Image 1 (tube, helix red, strand yellow):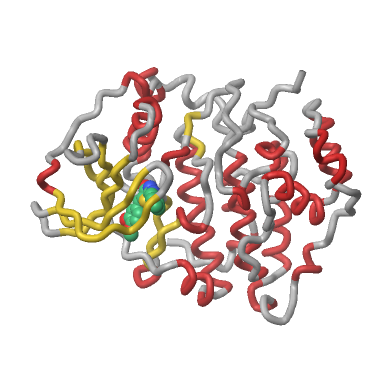
Image 2 (cartoon, rainbow, N blue to C red; image 1 turned 180 degrees about the horizontal axis):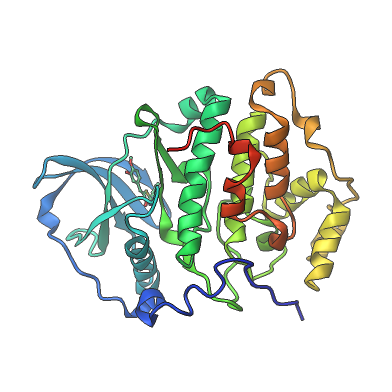
Length: 328
Ligand SMILES: COc1ccc(/C=C2\S/C(=N\c3ccccc3)NC2=O)cc1O
């Protein structure tokens, strides 16, 4: 069978919490007043919800209303409990309220509103310093939720709301997030394809917080190199082949050999043999201004096959890449 794995940090956080903290199936939702919130315009539709900009008429302030499509009560309470546990943490989106939507017949989460700059203007104009700044702001959020027993499992540009005017960042969409318990086997069908960690792509279920750091590396590579997404697979199989053309196939085999994992035989025809590449290969005159030796070394230490060898969020915040960022 496969070799078990545990997180190298925050391993026992949920163990020594009261069972109330992580036993989300037992959570009792405390409902607000649906009539306090007036929908203004639809902002998005996902597979699991729709999201609206709205007004809270008791303070005339804008809020964002996420009305869940029908989903199992378990998963609704999971998201709710996680939002409540993490509320007030650095750069975590704030759950303001929860109300019963009369039309949907499902819960509606009420969030703080972020005046977000949308993501193509952000991708096109963020400077070297801005990338470092916002990376640091993201690591603050990730170190907080990891220290609180929670992995996000869906880190990607669209879940990072930035109001670039006020240099304000918020990590959103906790609907895939889970509590980390040592030895617990999880569902590998999480994260968007381009940000899925190798552990997911080789069907290794006993993963942990370090999955978020792989996804964060994919975001970082897309920004400093100006290739979004960076690993652009046509499906989950070709996703792993795209990674292996950069990180090499020899270390991929070392990885699965360490955990006594076996690749799906369907890779036999498509994986090939690939050397590991130096990151300088992706540097050119149109992304040069975003690359430094520090950037490449930091990236290199995030994008590791072995989830156990990636930097933790806290370790990443110690990296020289962030020495130039003004600390508050
Ligand atoms: C414009 O400002 C905001 C925008 C979004 C959120 C929070 C969200 S959005 C979400 N899920 C989605 C996303 C896209 C489509 C459908 C559902 N989950 C969250 O927590 C908070 C904001 O202040």
